[PDB]
């Protein structure tokens, strides 16, 4: 298992997702939430963008899976969420 599933949920995938699945889930999520779309939702679009950035990086994904989102963010670049 994983500590938290939110990021996987945001992309519409299992916590055991592979790279192809992460990319497909991100593409689908981005298409829903992009601010220029009728279903746009800026705050959710930020969340999905972070979810893909973390989960598609094998190192950050391991950190997330073992320690959670706040841990994965801690110490990160100041521009990030």
Image: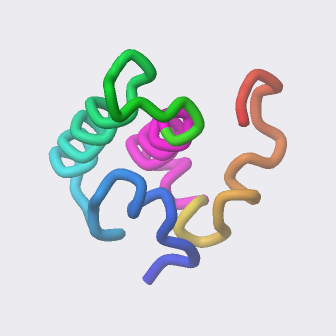
Q: Nearer the viewer, residue 47 or 56?
A: 47
Q: Is residue 36 above or below residue 81?
A: above
Residue lying at the far top in this picture: please name it: 36
Depth check: give the residue in front, 42 or 11. Answer: 42
16, 41: nearer the viewer: 41
Residue 39 in the image: above or below residue 67: above
Residue 4 rendering spot, x and y as whole percentages:
55, 73
Q: Please tell me which residue is depicted at 41% across the width and 30% down the height of the picture.
A: 40
**Left or right placement of residue 81 versus residue 32 in this view:** right
Residue at far front of view: 38
Identify the residue at image location x=34%, y=51%: 11
| Quadrant holding the C terminus | top right
Residue 44 point in image, percent of width and height = 51, 41
Horizontal and vertical percent for residue 1?
43, 83
Q: Main secondary structure of the magenta part?
A: helix
**Which residue is at a point 75% across and 58% down the rendered structure image?**
70
Q: Is residue 51 magenta?
A: yes
Query: On screen, 68 above or below 72?
Result: below
Residue 80 in the image, given as x and y percentages of width and height: 71, 30
Residue lying at 30% horizontally and 36% vertically, measured from the top left: 32
In the image: residue 81, left or right of residue 55: right
Residue range (magenta): 45-63
In the rendered view, does 29 fall on the left or right side of 72?
left
The colour scheme used to paint the residues is rainbow
Q: Is residue 8 in the magenta section?
A: no
Q: How many marks?
A: 0
Residue situated furthest bottom in the rendering:
1
Dividing the picture into quadrants, the one containing residue 38 is top left
Which one is nearer the viewer's eye here, 41 or 3?
41
Q: Which quarter of the picture shows residue 43?
A: top right
């Amino acid at each position: 298992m994983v500590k938290e599933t939110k990021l996987y949920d945001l992309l519409g995938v299992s916590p055991s997702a592979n790279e192809q699945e992460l990319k497909k889930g991100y593409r689908k999520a981005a298409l829903k939430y992009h601010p220029d779309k009728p279903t746009g939702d800026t705050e959710k679009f930020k969340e999905i963008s972070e979810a893909f950035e973390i989960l598609n990086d094998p190192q950050k994904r391991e950190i997330y899976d073992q320690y959670g989102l706040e841990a994965a963010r801690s110490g990160g670049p100041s521009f990030g969420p």
